[PDB]
Image 1: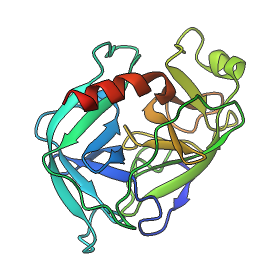
Image 2: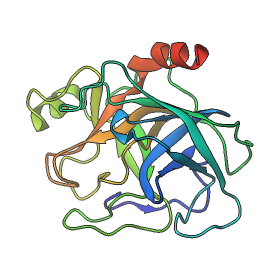
Image 3: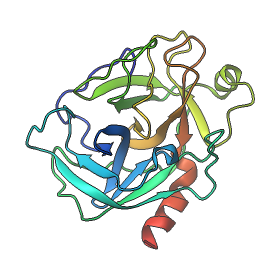
Length: 223
């Protein structure tokens, strides 16, 4: 997260870290046994870490649960990142509490201007790279359709939306992958892609979760 701020220990209970001997992506807890992330965050043997703040230090409130299966959307396009969503089922149900809680899926898409909360342990610099210990936050508004399409000419599909600041300086970055974009208590987006990080006219492009609610429900139910 570029230009964000320390969220504060477990102030984003639904935020999770995908681990492969190291943090490589973010994720959102949607129920005691399922996590929503980006399809580009796929890999075998992922270990989900819940209740994390300082990913470099075991603080005592974490729950490490191996993913029993990571299901990428059937229509995921690796080149464009169209349909960049993935469901991860936990080998076992997480113990939900004040530091480990799920986020509600949307029942309708968010309007331009809707301010959201984006979080993650990604790269904190727009040039080069520096990773934080604790979870970083960022309040960013959803960008209008036209401004989104102008920034990424012909690269924005209906399963994507922009959010951030066109003047740059504040944005998500590599490491935030799969992380949440919560607006009014609803997970409306997933950290997907973008041109650089925090560049002017190059805001974060996020997976439009509202478009995948039926798929998510259908996948969770038959798994």
